[PDB]
């Protein structure tokens, strides 16, 4: 190596979100180690080793904003890989925008955003909850049954459920419940009683709980008899193979997810991701969509740097649009709206905590940041390649 570049990593390693975010740091570090082993990042004929600073967001959104300022100003990083909850991202967004910096954010979310200073590898709703909703209503064993929505009390679950309510109405179904718990809250018995009352003949439960309150939720719904055997099916948007392995797959068997990457994808690229992750971190370790999303961020950033011949975040962000990567999920591409074109999978959870893949799109789906079911965003798009279009413009 001729020089070094130091990037920022900002995730919850402690608190209620650690169950989800800790493995993202592991995965981002694996990508960095791979890139370094292959020669680093090439800029102006010089090979740069990638170093990193990890900051603990501690499941606390003001801390995410504070550590973002530290990484940008004190540490002079050219990108921060970070975030999970939309609460943490909304807290960080003014920091990256006011400092004209660059956050790369990997987690599935609600859309309704298109920051010039954020790029996104997590699913937008049309890459996750919209196909999942149609699947539950039309194809699942609870086809035609009513929907009950349960999530954490912040902007992702509330916005996701607003979209779901619009879509279920358009599909001709019914929503019979919508309830939120504060993030981390484990007092799930009252909502369980409501689900039993509202779905006396079984049905679909849409779960947007984030973090480790999912542990209490899945264990208590099983003890209450809200089980696939009794006609109750949960579709979850914010947990996958990692959290399932901590919870215990016996509590998730038979329930559903919708994701762009699943560990069970039967391709050399998917198997190599899993095998490499186990070799570095242990044979017990899972890979999953959040990790695949974060992995991709590092490789996409590296490609954009080499295309731009610069680490400057304005030049890298300009170069990043259009970049393609042969990812563990299949081919992905960074779009003019800064999001990622991705293949969509529907899965049913097995006794071992893997997904049985039941549906898969014919190639990747372009991300709709501005949601096309929600009346306020219908007809809008985002395109940062055209000065006359931009963050939010009418088609
Ligand atoms: Ca920890
Ligand atoms: Ca993704
Ligand atoms: Ca199959
Ligand atoms: Ca858009």
Image: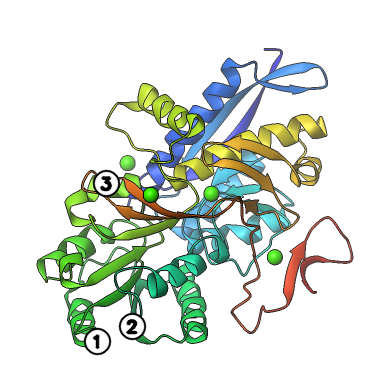
**Point 34% across, 49% down: residue:** 356
In the rendered image, residue 365, in percent from the top left (x then y), is placed at 62, 56
SS state under label 3: loop
Q: Is residue 38 left or right of residue 174?
A: right
**Point 12% across, 70% down: residue:** 225
**Which labelled disc corresponds to residue 146?**
2
First-in-chain label (2 vs 1): 2
Q: Which residue is mark 1?
A: 198
CB-based contact (under 8 Å), mark 2 and mark 1: yes
**Other-residue count near label 2 (Cα within 10 Å), few / some / many at <14 / 14–19 / ≥20:** many
Q: Nearer the viewer, mark 2 or mark 1?
A: 2
Q: Which residue is mark 3?
A: 353
In the rendered image, residue 288, in percent from the top left (x then y), is placed at 41, 44
**Point 65% across, 54% down: residue:** 339
SS state under label 1: helix
Quadrant of the drawing holding the C terminus: bottom right
Residue 156 in sight: yes
- Where residue 378 sits, quadrant-wise, is bottom right
Ligand 3 contact, mark 2 (Cβ < 8 Å): no
Q: Is residue 198 left or right of residue 9?
A: left
In the rendered image, residue 175, in percent from the top left (x then y), is placed at 38, 85
The correct choice, above or below, for 48 with respect to 114 in the image is: above
First-in-chain label (3 vs 2): 2
């Amino acid at each position: 190596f001729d020089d070094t570049v130091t990037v920022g990593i900002l995730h919850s390693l402690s608190g209620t979100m650690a169950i989800s975010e800790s493995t993202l740091v592991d995965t981002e570090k694996m990508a960095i180690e791979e890139i370094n082993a292959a020669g680093g990042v090439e800029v102006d004929g010089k090979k740069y080793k990638i170093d990193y600073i990890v900051e603990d967001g501690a499941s606390d959104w003001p801390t995410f904003a504070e550590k973002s300022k530290k990484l940008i100003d004190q540490d002079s990083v050219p990108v921060v890989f970070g975030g999970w909850t939309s609460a943490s991202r909304k807290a960080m967004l003014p920091v990256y925008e006011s400092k004209n910096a660059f956050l790369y954010y990997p987690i599935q979310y609600e859309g309704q955003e298109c920051s010039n200073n954020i790029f996104y590898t997590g699913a937008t709703p049309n890459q996750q909850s919209e196909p999942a909703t149609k699947f539950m209503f039309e194809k699942s064993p609870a086809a035609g049954k009513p929907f009950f929505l349960v999530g954490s009390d912040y902007v992702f679950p509330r916005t996701s459920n607003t979209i779901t309510k619009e879509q279920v109405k358009a599909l001709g179904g019914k929503v019979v419940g919508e309830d939120y718990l504060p993030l981390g809250n484990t007092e799930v018995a009252p909502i369980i009683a409501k689900i039993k009352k509202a779905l006396p003949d079984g049905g679909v439960i849409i779960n947007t709980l984030n973090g480790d309150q999912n542990v209490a939720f899945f264990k208590q719904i099983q003890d209450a008899g809200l089980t696939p055997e009794n006609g109750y099916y949960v579709m979850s948007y914010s947990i996958a193979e990692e959290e399932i392995s901590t919870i215990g797959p016996e509590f998730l068997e038979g329930h559903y997810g919708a994701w762009n990457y699943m560990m069970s994808i039967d391709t050399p690229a998917s198997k190599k991701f899993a095998s490499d992750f186990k070799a570095k971190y242990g044979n017990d370790r899972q890979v999953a969509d959040p990790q695949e999303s974060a992995y991709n961020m590092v490789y996409l950033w590296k490609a954009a740097v080499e295309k731009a011949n610069s680490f400057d975040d304005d030049k890298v962000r300009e170069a990043l649009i259009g970049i393609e990567f042969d990812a563990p999920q299949g081919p992905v591409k960074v779009m003019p709206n800064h999001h990622l074109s991705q293949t969509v999978r529907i899965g049913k959870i097995t006794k071992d905590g893997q997904f049985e893949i039941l549906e898969e799109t014919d190639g990747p789906v372009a991300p709709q940041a501005w949601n096309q079911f929600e009346p306020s965003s219908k007809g809008y798009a985002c395109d940062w390649t055209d000065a006359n279009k931009g963050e939010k413009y009418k088609l």
